[PDB]
Amino acid sequence: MTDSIMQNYNQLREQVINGDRRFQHKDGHLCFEGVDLDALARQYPTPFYVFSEPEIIRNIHEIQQAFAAHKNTKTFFASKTCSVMGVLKAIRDAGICAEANSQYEVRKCLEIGFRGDQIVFNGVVKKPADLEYAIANDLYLINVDSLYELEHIDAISRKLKKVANVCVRVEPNVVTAFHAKSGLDLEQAEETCRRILAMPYVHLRGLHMHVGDQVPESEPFAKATKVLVDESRRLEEVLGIKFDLINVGGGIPVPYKYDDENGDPLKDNMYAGITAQDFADAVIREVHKWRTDVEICIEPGRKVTGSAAVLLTEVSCEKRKTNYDLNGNVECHVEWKFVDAGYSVLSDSQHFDWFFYVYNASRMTAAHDAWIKLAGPLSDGGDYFHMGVKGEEFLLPKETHVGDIVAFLDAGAYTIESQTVYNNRPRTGVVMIDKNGDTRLIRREDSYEDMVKYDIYLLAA
Amino acid sequence: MTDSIMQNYNQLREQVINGDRRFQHKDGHLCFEGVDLDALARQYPTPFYVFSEPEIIRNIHEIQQAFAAHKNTKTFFASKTCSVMGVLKAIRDAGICAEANSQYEVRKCLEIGFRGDQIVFNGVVKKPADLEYAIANDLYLINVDSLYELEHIDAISRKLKKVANVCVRVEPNVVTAFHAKSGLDLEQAEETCRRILAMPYVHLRGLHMHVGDQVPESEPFAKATKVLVDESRRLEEVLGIKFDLINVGGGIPVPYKYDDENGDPLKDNMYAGITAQDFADAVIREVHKWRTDVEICIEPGRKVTGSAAVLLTEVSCEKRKTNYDLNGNVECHVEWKFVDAGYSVLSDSQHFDWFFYVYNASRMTAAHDAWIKLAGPLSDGGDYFHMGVKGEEFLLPKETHVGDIVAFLDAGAYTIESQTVYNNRPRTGVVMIDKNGDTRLIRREDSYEDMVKYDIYLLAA
Ligand SMILES: [Cl-]
Ligand SMILES: [Cl-]
Ligand SMILES: [Cl-]
Ligand SMILES: [Cl-]
Ligand code: NA
Ligand code: NA
Ligand code: NA
Ligand code: NA
C-alpha cells in the first residue's frame, strides 16, 4: 500500500529530526550537528557534500568500543573510502591509523600526518616504483598479494637496505579462484612465508584477509578468520616463529535503510545485517582460540565515514510529464524534480544501485506526501535516481519548489573520489563541520580552468 | 564449444591486423595508423588512451556521406562523448559543428575555435548563469527542455537585449512519462511554440528530439522523427510560420562486436544493428514527407570517436589461483593477468557492461590460445573485466608475460571524462595520432599535486 509506504517513510523522517544523534530541525530546516543545512547551502554553491567530524568520531568510537575484549587492536581507516585531506585529518586526530591503496594514497596519508608506522599499503598491482616509495617510508605493513610481487619486494628491499614489513594476504575458499582476484591461495601460504623468512630485508608479520564490503552477516567473518587463524597457528609451529599480528580487513556494514523490521539484509544489503560489535565478536572469538596477546589489525572503511556526510543539492528545475491514452484522456502524471547533482556527483546511486535516504532539507518538518521522480542535470536519459522509496519514486512535500535544498543522507563513503567531470560538470566542493560546530570548505569545486588545465592544445589568444 | 569460440576469436584477431582500415602489424605488434602500439607504450607511461585523427575523419565521412540525399544537413558532435581539447580540435578541423551539455562544455567549444553559430547547447538543468553565458555568446541553438526553463530564457534574453535561438525538445511517446526525464510532451509543443513567438528576444527555430544511445534498429528513429515532422508541419500551418530546422539528435551505434553473423543486436547491443546510412535513410525519408529544403540538424556523439581510440595498458602482475577439492586434488586453475587500468580508467566496462575487444598488442600475431581472467589494479574485488570473450574469460597468448601491452579497441567514446581518481590512481594521459601519423600528448596523466590541489588543509611543511 502506497499510503502505508508513505506513512512509514514519514515516520522515518520524523525519526531523523527527533531521534537521530546526527540531526535536529530549526526554522523548518534539517540541521546536522546544529548546522542548518538550508542556510549552509545558501553559503556554498550546490551541489556539495558536508561532513561531520563529530559523527566520524562517534563511528570510530563504535568500532574501538566493539574491540574492548582485545586490548592489542590496531585500526586502519581504509582511505579508498574517502581521502579528502580534511577528512583524513579528522580521522588522524580521532586517534586511529590509515590503510592506503596506491602510492599516492600512501603519500597523502604521510603528508596529512600519519606516520609510516600507522600506514598499511595494500594492493594487487604494486609496481617497483610503488614498492620503493613504500619501503623507503618504513610503512607498518605492505601486503604480499602474489608471488610475482614478492620478488620485487625482495629485490627492492635489498637495494634500499631497508626492511620491508609484510603481511601475506590469503583469501580462503569459504568460487574464490574465479571470483577473487586478490591474495594467495591458502595452499601457497606456507612456502611464501618460508621464503620471506629467508629474505634479509623482508620481515614477515602475519597473514591478511579482507572479506568484502557491506557484509550483512557475521558468519563470513567468523569462517574466514578461522581459516587464517588456523593457518597462523600451524605456521608458527611448522616454521618455529611467533607472528606479530593478524590483519582481518574491513567490511563492517552501515545502515542505509533503518527500518530493520521491514528488511531482509541477505536480500537487500542496504539493511545492515550486523553491527561493529558483531564483527568484533566474530573476529576476537576466533583469534583468541589461538592467541590472546597477538595484535589484531582491522581495516574499516565505510563504517568510519558513511553515516558522516550529507549531499546537499538544489532543486533546479521541475516539469510534469503526462501519459495520455489514444483518446487524449490522462492515464497518469509524473512529477519530475531536477536537482543539480546527478550520477557524476553521486556515483553509487547509479552504478551500484545504492540507496540513500532523500528528504527536502528546506521543508524537513513538512509531510513528504507527493510521489515524484528525482532527476540529475546530466544530458543523459539514465541520469535520474532509480533507487526510490517505492520503485523509482521518491516522496517530497507537495509544496516542494525550485530553490529548495534536497539532502541525501549517509553520503560519506565512496562518494568523493568516484566523482567525474562527465558533461564537464565539476566535481563538488566539500565542507566540514568541526568538533566545535563550525564549518569550513575542505575541497573546492572544480573550476573551468580544471576542466582544461590537463589538456595540451594550441591556444587561440 | 570453447575451441570454436577460440577459433572464431582468432579469426577476428587476424581480421584486425589483415582487414581493418585502422590497424596493421609490425615486429609482431599491433599498429594503429602505422604507429607501433607496443613502442608507443614504452614512450608514454601506461595506462593511456591513443586517439586517431584519421579514424575520426573516416567516421565523420560515413556520417556526412550518409546524408548526401539532403544537402542542408548540419552535424553537431555531441561533446559529452569526448571533450579533450585536441579531440575537439580534430573534429573542428574535419569540418563539423559541436553540441554541448553544460556551461563549461560551451566554453571549451568556443575556446577551441567552434563559433557560436556552430554550437547547440542542450540540457535539462540550464541555470540562469548557464543561460546567460549561452545567450551572450550567440549560440546557434539552445534547446528548450521545460516550461520552467523557458521563463528564464525569456527573462534573460530581455535583460541582455540579445536574441536567444531555440529549438523545443519534444519527446514522443513511441512509458515516456515515467522513463524519459527530457523534453516536453507532444501535447505541450503548440502552446510552448505559441509563447516563444510572442517573446521579443527568443527566436523559435524548430523542434528537437534525441532517441538515445547505441540504438540497434532504424524504426525508433523513423517513428520518432515522424512524430516530430508531423507536429512541425501542423504547427507551421496553425501558427503561420516556416521553421528553420528540425533537430533529430544522435544515437548512431558503433560496432563493439564485429561478427554480426553470430549476434542479435536486439539482445546484445554491442552488435551495431544499423549503419549511419540506415539512420540517415530513416530520418531523411520522414523529413522529406514535409519539406526538402528545411535544415536537418543531427547530434552524433559515439559514432564520431568510438572506433577512433585504443586503451593501452601494461600487464603489471600475474597469478594462478587454484580451486582444490576436499581431498586436495585440483578442480580448476584460473590464470589472472593484472593490467594497470581498471574501472576508474575504463568506466563503462564495469558500470554499463560494455564489451571492448581485448588483444595482446605486444603479441598481436600470436595465437590467443589461453583462457585468462583480466584484472585491474584497484584494491576492490569487483575491479576486474567481466565482459569477456566467453563469460568472464578472455583469450591471450599462453606466452603472455608481465610487461606486455594489452589493447582495448573501440575505446574512444565516453572513456575520458568518466574516469575517476578512485584509490587515488590518476586519470590517464591521452595521446593523438595526427593526419601525418605523428604522435603527441594531448592530455597529461594527473599528477600527485592534482590529487590534493583541490583540497584545503593545514600543511605540515
Ligand atoms: Cl589504532
Ligand atoms: Cl510542466
Ligand atoms: Cl556541419
Ligand atoms: Cl601464482
Ligand atoms: Na545553488
Ligand atoms: Na626475512
Ligand atoms: Na608501463
Ligand atoms: Na519570438
Image: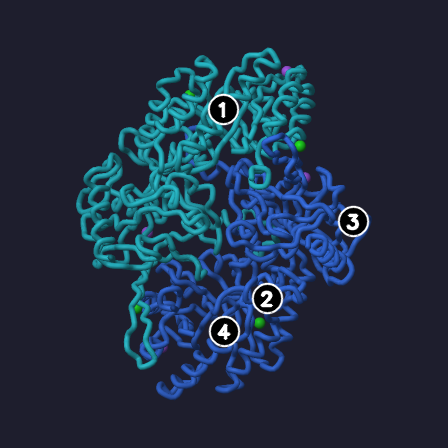
Chain colours: A cyan, B blue
Q: Nearer the viewer, residue B148 or B422?
A: B422
* Label 4 or label 3, whichever comes before in sequence order: 4
Could you tell me the amino acid type at mark 2?
A: Asp
Dot 1: what SS? strand
- CB under 8 Å between callouts 1 and 4? no
Tell which subunit mark 1 falls on.
Answer: A
Residue B218 position, x and y percent, is: 55, 74
Q: Which residue is mark 1?
A: A247
Question: Mark 3, residues whose alpha carbon is within 10 Å: few (<14), some, or many (≥20)?
Answer: some
Establish whether ligand 7 lies closer than 8 Å to the Cβ of label 3.
no
Residue A120 position, x and y percent, is: 51, 25
Q: Nearer the viewer, mark 1 or mark 4?
A: 1
Q: Which residue is mark 4?
A: B220
Establish whether ligand 1 lies closer than 8 Å to the Cβ of label 1.
no
Q: Which residue is mark 3?
A: B366
Q: Which residue is mark 2?
A: B264
Question: Mark 2, residues whose alpha carbon is within 10 Å: few (<14), some, or many (≥20)?
Answer: some
Give the vertical position of A170 relative to B136 (above or below): above
Is label 3 on the same chain as label 1? no
Tell which subunit mark 4 falls on.
Answer: B
Compute the Cα span from label 2 to label 4: 17 Å
Could you tell me the amino acid type at mark 1?
A: Asn
Question: Mark 1, residues whose alpha carbon is within 10 Å: few (<14), some, or many (≥20)?
Answer: many
Compute the Cα span from label 3 to label 1: 42 Å
Compute the Cα span from label 2 to label 1: 48 Å
* Label 2 or label 3, whichever comes before in sequence order: 2
Dot 2: what SS? loop
Tell which subunit mark 2 falls on.
Answer: B
